[PDB]
Length: 52
Length: 51
Length: 51
Length: 53
Image (tube, rainbow over all chains, first blue to last red; front, side):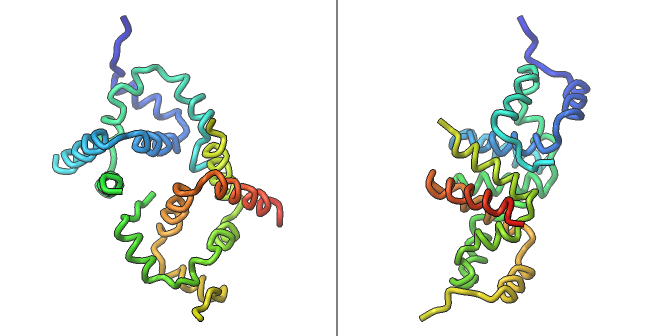
């Protein structure tokens, strides 16, 4: 029975106290752990994000 | 200050973060990046898509 | 971190000298201060350590 | 026979007209395709280069 969502302000405030580099060591290790489908899912989200 | 974080210490890091942090995490960070940043990320993705 | 496309990486390198590709790594690691050195140092370890 | 050695000045010259992001990109394409053997090689060598001040 534990909420699956992190409010913005709490997100923004946790990230303000993480080792800066973590935000690439994450994506690299994330993108590295993806498969084909995970990749187009990500490519497309990226695609959208640039058009918006 | 390292540019890369070691495995077991990055686990130390993640380990003291509630799951909520990671839920739709990929989404969020992607939500914040730059044009060249994400432009960069798109290329890698398109690369491994063929790589 | 700028990403260099699989096609922008290939292009360049084929226009690089065959001799340029000779033990680049010592030159590089030579042209790689201790800071860098340790970063990539750690990484190889991790890369290796994996059971 | 083709050369297989480049003077420190040609190398360096050839590096300055190289995109700033060539080496990091280059550095990990090598790494990524190294087996346990070469991995262990470069560590030992990074180690060696650690204290060869």
